[PDB]
Amino acid sequence: STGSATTTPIDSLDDAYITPVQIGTPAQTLNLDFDTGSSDLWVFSSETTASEVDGQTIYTPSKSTTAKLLSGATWSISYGDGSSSSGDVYTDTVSVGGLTVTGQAVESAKKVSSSFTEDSTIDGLLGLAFSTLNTVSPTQQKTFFDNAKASLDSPVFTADLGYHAPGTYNFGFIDTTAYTGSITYTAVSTKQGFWEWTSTGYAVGSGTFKSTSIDGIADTGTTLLYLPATVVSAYWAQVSGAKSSSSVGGYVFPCSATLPSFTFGVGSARIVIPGDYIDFGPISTGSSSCFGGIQSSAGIGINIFGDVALKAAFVVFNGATTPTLGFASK
């Protein structure tokens, strides 16, 4: 089997991407944030505290003839941005772009933090990291990809995120029309539960490539590109007037600037992030200070190849017995 679903930016900055997912019988379609940095499929639901729902579409398990309460199971998750959610668990039929998994754990939110309530466009998350990170207790549950893997034509999924435009998540096949050149594959460590890999270096604009190992995670659920402070300083030094602002929470730059590109290495290959992809717009409405798309990871503990980086590539998440990642230009 295969599946193919369009993913759409939630706003004009590409702050996140939503993909429609069918849950239950008859289908209830919710728009989920596919997150290769986490491993829970959780949804706003009929059980979510009413004051914490503000425009999201909810899953109502009582209206699904295939929903079954997973007795005794609970979940609770906290994300790198400080947001969180928790609740109980059903199993139900879940389909993505024509690919169906029966008995998928659907984690029903009883509580969500304010950032989730405040984002009416995201109805939940669909985690695509390794199932060892799944938070369901006392019996850990498998991701949608893990459940579908054996049925897929090939044990892979691909992320093709658009810049200010829709893109595609495919399951079970590699669309050879979706990228240019060849796909360069690189080793993955699953030791932290992430799609963790080592970039071979970087360049700023037309500058020379610096060969240096940068360990980080391919994370579709993180908006920006978080890299070591040395690398980020070297990038922003090429932008007149850019500075790190403690009050804003990162590098800002004059909105009148033209940003340089940023290149990252994948083995001997190179992925170029155009400068425009690094502009996240005014820090507040009407400001002429703009927020940068490349930020320091120094306060995180890990480097994160988020959407800013991934949207410049066609990315293969290869879930073979030894997983690998592939990157192509497009």
Image (cartoon, grey):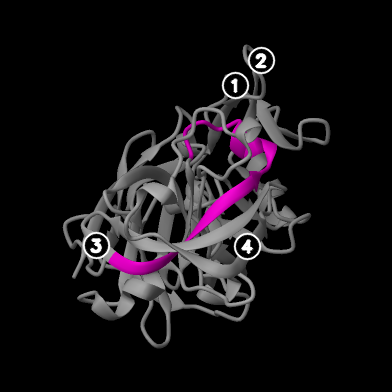
Judged by depth in the image, the label closer to the viewer, 3 or 2, is 3
* Range of residues picked out in magenta: 101-122
Q: Secondary structure at mark 4?
A: strand
Which residue is found at the position 68% from the left and 46% from the top?
83
Q: Amino acid at mark 1?
A: Cys
Q: Which residue is mark 3?
A: 99
Q: Which residue is mark 1?
A: 255
Judged by depth in the image, the label closer to the viewer, 2 or 4, is 4
Q: Amino acid at mark 4?
A: Trp
10 Å crowding of disc 2: few (<14), some (14-19), many (20+): few
Q: Secondary structure at mark 3?
A: strand
Residue 62 belongs to magenta span:
no
Residue 104 belongs to magenta span:
yes
Question: Any mark on residue 75, and which?
Answer: 4
Asked whether, in this view, residue 244 is left or right of residue 109, the answer is: right
Q: Position of residue 267 (x, y in %)?
A: 44, 73
Judged by depth in the image, the label closer to the viewer, 2 or 1, is 2
